[PDB]
Amino acid sequence: MGSSHHHHHHSSGRENLYFQGHMLEVEVISGRTLNQGATVEEKLTEEYFNAVNYAEINEEDWNALGLQEGDRVKVKTEFGEVVVFAKKGDVPKGMIFIPMGPYANMVIDPSTDGTGMPQFKGVKGTVEKTDEKVLSVKELLEAIGS
Image: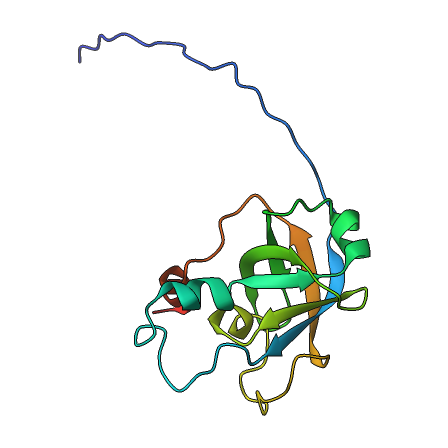
């Protein structure tokens, strides 16, 4: 028996703006700019964090998503997903170029030849404007299971 205590009623008035966007179906390419042969640990430098960390997007889709030079985008395929730096490129509409790396590895097929000069030919998928952070090279490793 016996019970006694005090109960507060606390809440918070918070401001919040919502966007609600629309993802575009794009072909995610992987061109060998950063040459492999080692691990991201063996090549633990800013080069690996600037080379394969961005996607080149067509002007039309760029405006369609409302991208600003400096934003980051979510890339999604049947293989997986990754957040990379949004950059503009001379690629065709509904298509984006990514340097062959761990970031691309999230959304592309790592079984194919993985060899070719940067012109076209990539893994189909989608891209959208997100508030998320770009997956740091190691954070990406931790995300895939390591």
